[PDB]
Image: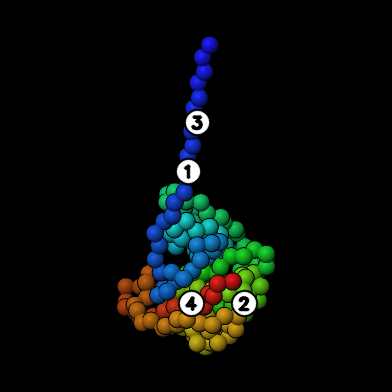
Amino acid sequence: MWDERFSQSEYVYGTEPNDFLVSVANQIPQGKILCLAEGEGRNACFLASLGYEVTAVDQSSVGLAKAKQLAQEKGVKITTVQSNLADFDIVADAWEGIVSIFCHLPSSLRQQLYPKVYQGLKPGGVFILEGFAPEQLQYNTGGPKDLDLLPKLETLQSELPSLNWLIANNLERNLDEGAYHQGKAALIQLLGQKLEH
């Protein structure tokens, strides 16, 4: 005649440190983030390392593959979708913030994206744009057909009604990945206002 009693338990939970991307992008939610035209998705994996759920969309499958490779190397999970942003369908129920890193694209696409991202992201959401400007075309080519077709940030921020802007700066810097010969370039950084939904 004998008896024995015992039990066990455990708890797994923690968070990761973070920081602003632009100036105040630390106001970006830790939730689901949609990153468009990222090319390599380096910042996408960076966001994932912050504990963020990151979806990356690009026209380049190999660029998305680079994002996947980066994610694996960083030990984080990432989602990739191959699609042209012009044809890409953003679903309203699909609540994901909008981040553009160094996305060289025609303003006409933004006009098409505007309705997509507005309906896609819940009210009070935030839109992020950071990187060189198309005006960088003045370095080499003078434009896709013309520099005149290229949007300034003042145009972009004025053409985007869905949110109010907290920050917007035009920065002067030498063009990265250019020719041997020097060459200045304009960079655009601006961030929309997020109020708790």
Q: Position of residue 23 (x, y in %)?
A: 40, 75
Question: Label 2 belongs to which residue?
Answer: 114
Disc 1 residue type (three-letter): Tyr
Q: Residue at x 66, y 73 (%)?
A: 119
The C terminus - image quarter: bottom right
Badge 1: how crowded within 10 Å, few (<14), some, or many (20+)?
few
Please determine whether, in this image, residue 161 is positioned above or below residue 87. below
Question: Label 1 belongs to which residue?
Answer: 11
State the CA–CA distance, disc 2 to disc 4.
15 Å
Question: Label 3 belongs to which residue?
Answer: 7
Disc 4 residue type (three-letter): Leu
Please determine whether, in this image, residue 154 is positioned above or below residue 29. below
Badge 2: how crowded within 10 Å, few (<14), some, or many (20+)?
some
Disc 3 residue type (three-letter): Ser
Question: Label 4 belongs to which residue?
Answer: 191
State the CA–CA distance, disc 1 to disc 3.
14 Å
Disc 2 residue type (three-letter): Tyr
Q: Residue at x 51, y 78 (%)?
A: 192
Do labels 2 and 1 touch, CB within 8 Å? no
Q: Residue at x 37, y 75 (%)?
A: 175
In this rendering, the label closer to the viewer, 4 or 1: 1
In what element is the residue under mark 4?
strand
Badge 3: how crowded within 10 Å, few (<14), some, or many (20+)?
few
Toward which corner of the image does residue 195 lie, by quadrant?
Answer: bottom right
In this rendering, the label closer to the viewer, 1 or 3: 3
